[PDB]
Structure formats: structure tokens, C-alpha cells
Image (tube, rainbow over all chains, first blue to last red):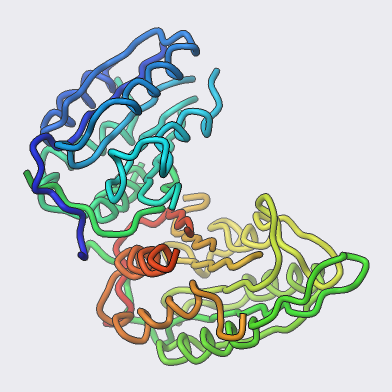
Length: 170
Length: 196
């Protein structure tokens, strides 16, 4: 009970929003490099992100272990996107984590965040360089705090409303 | 190394601000059980090498003037630094006996440029309210104490010397959610266990 369960078919479905391309392409490879069902979206007319998310919120993740999403900007409210995956709002994701990665320029338990700001950026450049190398053998926090170390060698916060540790088995 | 340096003379300070009785003009309830909430934390961090100092029913000017004077100290022989708040709070703001000060104003005193004595050192902050900002961590959260506090030390005197803070805080988040949620915002750069 000290880590999140991983006896699941799919790892999870990864969503990538890309308003505007190196970071996206690099995030794609490195997240599929964990075993993610990755889907990329560009030129997202702000009406998209809403319906785009809610769809996935009404999908089935019973045979999925988790769920990740990534935003890339430079107009859509933060909370109005995440609330689709509330406690009751998406019952297929309970006792399952929700991971939102951001870079621009009961309920609410088991959520994680990471917002960065500005070739491509550092944060991104830094992250993949870990997930490729130490991706499948670290707890999530052990990873992000390593990224903050890497970017500081040249800062993005990290909201953790999680309940157990997070490595990446099957 | 992939973790914070603990080989220091002393650990660090541990300012506790126990706000219980606020003024009437604030129209703010008397936060009860907070004496227990403080004593629990004080006893806990005491047993972790924190030189614990407990402040009580302070004004906003006090809480401001206090931390500033503590930021301007010599923290060189100290590994880290902690500060725990107990009061009423709202949207990124926290009550004093007299008024209301923005939380980001209190912590600002320690921002690496204005507290060089704590640079590359973790500067912690615990909130229970009813390399700019690097090395910062924030953990915002009856008869017995609160859940959070009681559950924290419950895990902290038990595992605190042998677990990383996230391992500690993530653990805390489970037992509070077990009863029925706190948000741990981290800007750290290295893992942090509470021993040598």
C-alpha cells in the first residue's frame, strides 16, 4: 500500500496540447519511452481543450494504471480543465494518479503538477534526459527534484496532492 | 551527491506561530485545539534537532518583523530552516491577531538573494490555516489536534529519521484522506532525509 498499483494492461493515456515543436516531438518519444498511449494536438482553439479533455474523462481507464497530460502555450483557465477528472467526475480514475505537466510563456486527491516558463527549453530537455535513463526505476518526486537541480545548473514549482509513491512497473 | 547536506553544526531553526485568540474587529473564531496542535509539533521537531521557538497570538507586523529578523540571522552552521503556521487563512493569505498578511510576503524574506545564509539550503514552510525561490517547500493543509498535525507527527517520530520529506508528506496525505487533502508545493533541488 506504499506505492501505486501497476498490475494493469496499459500504463496510461498521455495527452499533449501544443499551441504555436522540438519539445513536443521530444516529449512524445520520451513518454512513449515509458509505455504511454500518447496523442498530440496542435493549434488548439481554446474550445478544443475543453471537449478534448472531457472526452477522455468519459472514456474507460479500467485496464489503465494512470493518466498523464501535457500543455504547451505562450487562452484557457487552469482549473476549468482539471476538474473533469474530479473524484466522481471520472470514477475510472480513483486510487489512480492524474499527472498534469505544464509549460507556458475525496476529490483533488492523487493529482500532480509541474509548471515551467520561458533549440527547445531546459525543463523539457532536462526531463526526457532522465526518463530515458532513470525513468522506470525512480519515484516521481525523486525525478522532478532532479530536474530542478538540472535546470538550476543553468524554476518550476511542483504541486503534489498524491497519496502513495510512484514508480513505473508494467 | 543526490541529496541535501546534513553535515552541519546545528540543523536549523523552527519558528512556530500559534495564533489562537484573534481580535474581535477581525470577526474571527477562536481556533481551538491549536494549543494541542502546537505542543505536538513542538515536541516532534524538538526530537529532530530543530531548536524550536513558539510564538503566540501575534500581530501581522510581528509575524512580518519576526521572520525578517530570523532571515537576517546567521544560518551558516545550520543545515536547513523550518517555519510552521497555525491560524486562519484564505486565498494565499493568512490571519494575524490584528489583520491579514499575504503569505508570499512572509516567506519572501528568505528568497536566496535576501537570505544568502540559507542559499543552497532547504527553507521549509508548513501551513495549517482554517535560484530565486529555489530550495523552497510548502505544505499547506477539535478536542484532539487536527488530523494533519496529529497524523504528521504520528508518521514523523516514527519514520522521520529514515524517510525523505515527500515519502513523509505523501504518507501524511494518505492518512488524512483515509479518515474521510493538503497540497505539497516543492521547489527543491535534492532529496532530503532528516539524518546524517
